[PDB]
Image (cartoon, rainbow over all chains, first blue to last red; front, side, top):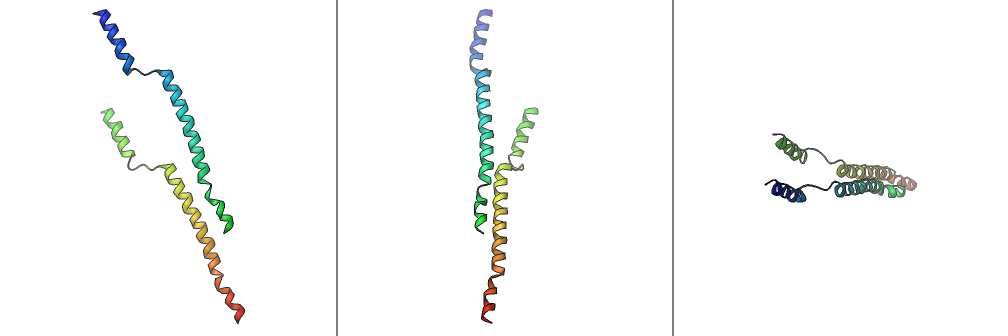
Length: 55
Length: 55
């Protein structure tokens, strides 16, 4: 029973439990993309005033 | 209770809380349109001055 319990616990942890490294790398990549996207949205926000010189 | 509270708070924020990025673009476009309208109104105000040369 003890042997089967440890084997079953390992099998269950193989599914539900997350891998911390493979999650942290994705989290860092996503946050880098978020800051790049918000900077570029800010850049896009200051595009349309180019035509104000024509007024 | 705490799970339900966090879910309900998320649902409430999905409705009443505003999106800052989605709204700042509209704000900047609006003020650009205001500047263009002010410029055009100023230009149209001096429009009838051309008739003075006929008097």
